[PDB]
Length: 271
Ligand SMILES: [Cl-]
Ligand SMILES: [Cl-]
Ligand SMILES: [Cl-]
Ligand SMILES: [Cl-]
Ligand SMILES: [Cl-]
Image (cartoon, rainbow, N blue to C red; front, side):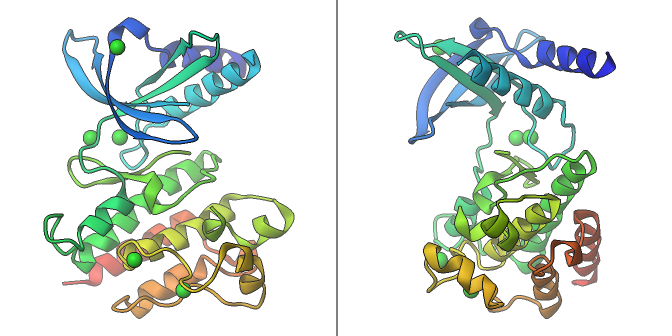
């Protein structure tokens, strides 16, 4: 059918020939896998700087399908997936590679922390912190409109592009909504909860959520109605917006389209 055909097309489009890519230095490494700098030879004969993230036949197929879907996203505030390559290890283990644009400014969380150091970016003014929030809201609004759930929204998974536009990427107890802690159920409103926490990371310029509270204590902390505290120098109206994201009942939380307009309005009002 059309659904099957659509997926077949996306699959064709997402794979990149291993020989159009060369891998460079490791930029980061963990239990999940690696990030390396790379070069991608493009259709026009010129090479592009890329970031390359490395991680059963079903698990490979699932990766491929998921990647196929993700490449299809087309929004300035959603990371553009350039494609994927599957290289096989010497021990016959598949090595799936995600190719992405190289972003010299890195993730938003690290950037916020650097901005509090002398060598890093200058003190980020309120208006710019808010613009970061609008951008993320715009990306999450897009995803939500196509019923895609992010499931790992946090400032560390938002990327800064060369023009300082933020995009959501990488689709963590202190980001998880109360209902997902309880019933392991996760909806678009759970992403909205994560977005509120992310807004708080931005307003605190990179603080870890819930200082003084440990991960194992989180469910009970939230259970007794405690939430993230208003950051110093955070507008009361901005705090109300982020607090709305943590309403106990998912259905009372605003949608991303509503949040986005609230945030845009607030930004407009600043001089
Ligand atoms: Cl190579
Ligand atoms: Cl991008
Ligand atoms: Cl970029
Ligand atoms: Cl901190
Ligand atoms: Cl707090």
